[PDB]
Amino acid sequence: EASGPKSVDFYQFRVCSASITGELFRFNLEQTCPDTKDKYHQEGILLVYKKNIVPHIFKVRRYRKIATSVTVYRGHRESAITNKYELPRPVPLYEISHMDSTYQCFSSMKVNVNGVENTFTDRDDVNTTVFLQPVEGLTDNIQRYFSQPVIYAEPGRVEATYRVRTTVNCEIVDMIARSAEPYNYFVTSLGDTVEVSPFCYNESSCSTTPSNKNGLSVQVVLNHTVVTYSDRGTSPTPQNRIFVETGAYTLSWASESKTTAVCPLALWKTFPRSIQTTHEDSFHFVANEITATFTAPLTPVANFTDTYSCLTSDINTTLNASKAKLASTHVPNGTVQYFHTTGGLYLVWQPMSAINLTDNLSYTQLQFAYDKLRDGINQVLEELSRAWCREQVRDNLMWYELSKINPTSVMTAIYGRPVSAKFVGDAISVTECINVDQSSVNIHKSLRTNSKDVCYARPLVTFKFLNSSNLFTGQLGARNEIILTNNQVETCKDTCEHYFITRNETLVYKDYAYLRTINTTDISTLNTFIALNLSFIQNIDFKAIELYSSAEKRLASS
Amino acid sequence: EASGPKSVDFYQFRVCSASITGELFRFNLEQTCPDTKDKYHQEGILLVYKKNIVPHIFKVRRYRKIATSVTVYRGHRESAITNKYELPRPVPLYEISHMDSTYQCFSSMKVNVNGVENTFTDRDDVNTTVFLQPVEGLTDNIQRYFSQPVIYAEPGRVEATYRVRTTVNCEIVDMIARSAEPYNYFVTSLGDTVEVSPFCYNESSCSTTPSNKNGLSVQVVLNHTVVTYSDRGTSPTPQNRIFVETGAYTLSWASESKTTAVCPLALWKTFPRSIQTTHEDSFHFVANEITATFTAPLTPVANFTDTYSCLTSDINTTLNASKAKLASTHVPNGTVQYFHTTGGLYLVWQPMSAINLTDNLSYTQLQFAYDKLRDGINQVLEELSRAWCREQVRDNLMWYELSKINPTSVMTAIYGRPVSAKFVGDAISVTECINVDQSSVNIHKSLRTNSKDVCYARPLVTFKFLNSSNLFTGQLGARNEIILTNNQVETCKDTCEHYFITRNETLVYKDYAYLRTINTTDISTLNTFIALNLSFIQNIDFKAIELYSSAEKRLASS
Amino acid sequence: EASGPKSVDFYQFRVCSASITGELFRFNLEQTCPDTKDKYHQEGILLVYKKNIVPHIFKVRRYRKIATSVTVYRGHRESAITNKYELPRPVPLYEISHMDSTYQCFSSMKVNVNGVENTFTDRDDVNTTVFLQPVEGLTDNIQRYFSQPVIYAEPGRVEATYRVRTTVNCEIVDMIARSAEPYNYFVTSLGDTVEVSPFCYNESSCSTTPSNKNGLSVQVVLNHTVVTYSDRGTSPTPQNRIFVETGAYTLSWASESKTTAVCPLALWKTFPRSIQTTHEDSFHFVANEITATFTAPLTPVANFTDTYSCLTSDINTTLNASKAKLASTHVPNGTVQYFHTTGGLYLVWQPMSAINLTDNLSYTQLQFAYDKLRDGINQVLEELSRAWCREQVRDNLMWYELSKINPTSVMTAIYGRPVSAKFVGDAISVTECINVDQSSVNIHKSLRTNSKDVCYARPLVTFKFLNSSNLFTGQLGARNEIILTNNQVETCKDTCEHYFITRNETLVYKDYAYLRTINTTDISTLNTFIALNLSFIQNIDFKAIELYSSAEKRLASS
């Protein structure tokens, strides 16, 4: 019979009506797609905790001994001729400053010098007692106490060279001291600076009963029992205290432990409603009250949050208050957890389940905006996909309905390669197609057959079965296809017009016979397209903007 | 007849050809959707106003009296043996400093002491007049004036103990003072600090003719008429002035009101082109020159912008200049308005209508980017929806065209539930379908009927009308459907092959009679689907980045 | 014949079956769309370079002469009665400080005074030599050297007025000095401030052999050969040095050029993998390790990066190391380039080609996020467009397949205006349509014709050919269309029902004749629509958030 290569494109004349049954195909009349289930999200109370920066504040008492002399008797009687060194000295502990601590009196006429011990006073006893008194000042936190505040005698009489009048003074000053986070040194309000740790001699090292230091003393007293009330003596508890003897003054302050006094964690904000969304390797806590999102590693890095013993007595109260407020429509679902974000902030998470009726913080806002946009885009894509699936199902149903007329057209539409088909029972049977000798083609110039009013609907063709020596007569179909049975006939009509398509050339029949071959493109080609004039997203550039120039910053000064 | 439950799925054999007319349906041949109208947006000139931080600057004049003594005559003749207290004193107002104000001379030999009034001088008159003079220095803003600048006599002769030579000095210093925003205290360039308000005795309280203060004087003089020109005397206006007598010096400066001198609002930028878009409860002003967007509440919070009386004379000029520049293609459309953003910046809005031919600022940039992305996405969605509507209209038209062959298939395609329909006149009439007894089914194993070449196209079936005792003969259709009229016949063909679908089982007829029952899935099922391999949007994490570490910040120091 | 206006809508009765051939149209059986080619992107090593802010650090040596006296013999024998001026003086260059530089001895008894040269000492020779020695202190960077450290003699014997004991001291202090970026002035660690440039007398101006300045000296010495080792004398190289003689002390430091010592560019980070994407007028370098993107102008603004001569010896090493590490799978492709971003950072770009197997930084993160979102959206749009093109091609094929039954319906579906078409061979010919006289219309109330069981399928109509005086008989079709040939007949059926449509009115035929005219809307209209319930993107507002309030900032203090 006829054999050869199988057709793969609509460019070579081919004929195929073989009765050999091929593959069997059926239309999938049942098709559907489901709807995704909503992914529920956990919620609960979220608390943040920024790093504290407020310095530690405590009160400190200072003692200082002042000795001054005036020598103004130049000529007959001069005034303010010259002044002495006025060197101040630390208060000695000969009486352990017990009288000063009593805030009642003190021993004047201090004796101390680098060369030899010499007593300086107003010509009185070496260990005379002078009653202290408070002096008012232009300060609400410096209750200075003065003894012998008036200037020296300064006789100003007729003296040859100068006078020798001099007095001594005892000074008790109350001030406030502040220390940084490391708590290794602190500076008082007056201005003095000392390089010792405020926390010592109480659950801390670098302090002992003997007095010894590099330029200091660092002496600790057990149950000092400071009266601490010069205006009205009282009976306070003998609290512990320490002393530091500098080169010119002595400072005293109560001893306290580093723990249970100051720890670096302060509450910033509380969000009664928050959403936690898991991810590949991190969490996401949403706080829409300030439009920010905090990310933390999946593992609860704060596995030992019991070291921060301070907050164990306040985070409980805040959580209790928040859950009491939210108890109307929410209940706890699990144990509390502590996380640690990359920015240095600590998060406290307490998941809650609904009850059935029956300055570097810009990246958080950026993350929030990105998450919102991504969620919106994903939801839109999901809806579009569902609509497309429904449309595809309907389209397939139409296709099946259309296939009931001629399966060959539908099969050639679905598969790019031309094929052939027939409705075996209720099942399409697909067979391949076979070409013929392209050179051996002959088309009659007249479609008018014998008799009358029975003219052929399509021109008759003759060809050879490829690699064979034989001739057959067929009728030209469509897309360069040959049909063995020539049953296409029609009644003759006056001024009949006909056109045919054959690859890049066309045939024209103004009458029952014509060969006005013209180009295929000469006839207009209609289009059925719904253009999608989509507009892409332009890409822009961002520029840094500074509110205040460097000139204004310099002009700010201090 | 036959009655029972109505079919709801393609799983039970059913037959329905009832002549009772049901509901009437017609194809909506006319369908269309409109295009949304563009929402025009207001535009106009927008000006921002940041909070001023530049400190107030004004000139201040200082007067001070200096008395010093030198006693160097130790042994035979010593030098620099000792110095006096050199205590400086404020300039007294015995002459009301009129001579000093004249910048011509001053009264030397000042007499003042805490004990008793003693006059110190170079052994001259108590009220002797000494002419002032200017002294050059290494400063471009300190025109210090000195009288008696040379050191004391210091005889250095043969004296037993020391000398008594001493002189006095009058000092006039011109300096510059700066004050913070509250204007409650200020510090001069020299270094002195005073806790009085720079604005006083002129539209301000805390100032009166009597001199009285807590450690100060705060004296006001009416029409002081300061010459203010030591190099060349002039005749200036008698401007008002005030004085403050400290413990060692006196400061003077001209009095000015708090208003009309310094107010905290400075212009930052001007945008001749901006867009205002309304929202649910806020406005949105777009400034694309710096890629930022400012949001303000809907209500014009700056309802009393007349309090800032300073800007009423400059915002008018800037607006006039901008509108003069833009008058080529724009004209004003409404009255000016003032807003107040959440960040603390003040906005000035002046809408303009086109003329017909015939450091915390990152959130603004974030808002700008979010708005741009949202607008682009919304526009894309609108275009997609319009294209989808056009496609749906065309699809409905194609469905109506297809319905002209057999309405039953189209109706069963549109409605999931199988139905029976027909073309009454030019309107489809749909009727419900009725099942039969599933158990009472019988299919003949041979489709070859009597005579020859008239074999049945489909096998004949027999069943009972559900809840009834009767038998009927029908022909099997498709999707388990029965047809009463058995007119499906065809010419007998040798080696005829047939297949049929019945729920999960199939029938095979290799000849005019066969019962090779096989599974339905044995035959391949072709697919007609255009997969939408959409790619979702991945979610990433942002990390904080610091340009300079804390070590570099510490190394910066001052 | 019949002529008049051409129909443009389905609202007027029209008839058109003209034999005149119109335009020729053919179905474009071949249609396809291509897939976009991936745009490859360059990659290579990217290095950033922030502006350096670390101040310059160098060592400085200071010399100072101190003279002090004590006069304490008041009464019989007093102590610390008074002190002298203790005026310090700069070390003179009588010996050019050669002995001090030798760190072995120095000439005591300095003679200097404003009045007349007087020698002060401990009653010794004017040019006596005293050996220097080092004194320990509480500092790890101040190796102070002291000569005559003990206090003056202070006889304290029985003297009438006072003593005259006095001593002099030579001080050599080693300190560290730091200077800002402009390098015009610097301040030492001790506290002294000098307004001279650290870089002078070596590839710099403002320095010369003669000593002259405004209050200073600025003297340069060639090959000073400072021993610089008091603990153990050595033999160092005679390096150059300079001196500055202040009013009380002299400072010395080694001279160095501004270049080759300190230049303001420090490496911040290195990214072995980066992507460069071109744009309209700028580049885009992606560094996903910190999620940031840097933008630079298209032109290599750093066209003269050879001025920064420091980095030419280190950027080469870093690039060599990075390319050695990446040589496993990458090789260089071009020459190095230098860019300059808008934020003030400098970028170094070195493109690399893969080898074939055979604190203001938020805007960068914002740009990165925007670019990622834009790329994702664009990719999604491209995929959607490709899927839509495939669907459109399939739809057009289905339309062509459907057109084989009746071209009139397909043509009227594609073109809104009704037309008339008829297949012409392979192609088709579509003509226009002509209306008739709307008033001249008559529809028979009975569709039952002569004989029996041959009743008309559609009612017969009679009308006039618009602007003409004639009558014709036709059959009503669909959408107000008239057909000349009345061949629509059917067998008579009992209880026949027929509804027909006509603009806004309908006809009902309960029997072979009826005129129950009712409204068209009375019959239900079925719909075939797949709703696209797209959800738009909500627009939100961002609010500025401050981590630490101003109160905490004030409490931080210093």
Image: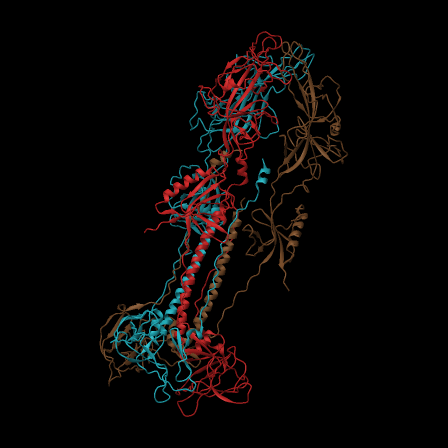
Chain colours: A red, B cyan, C brown
Residue C197 in percent (x, y) is at 66, 35
Residue B551 in percent (x, y) is at 59, 40
Residue A296 in percent (x, y) is at 49, 48
In the rendered image, the residue lying farthest to the bottom is: A451
Residue C5 shows in the view: no
Quarter of the image for residue C204 reads top right
Q: Is residue C525 above or below residue A131?
A: below
Residue B485 in percent (x, y) is at 30, 81
- Looking at the rendered image, the quarter that the C terminus of chain C falls into is top right
Q: Please give the count of numbered marks on the rendered protein.
A: 0
Q: Is residue B290 above or below residue A248?
A: below
In the rendered image, the residue lying farthest to the top is: A158
Choose between C466 and A505: the one closer to the eye. A505
Q: Is residue C159 above or below residue B209?
A: above
Residue B553 shows in the view: yes
Choose between C477 and A233: the one closer to the eye. A233
Choose between B116 and C146: the one closer to the eye. C146
- Looking at the rendered image, the quarter that the N terminus of chain C falls into is bottom left
Quarter of the image for residue A79 reads top right
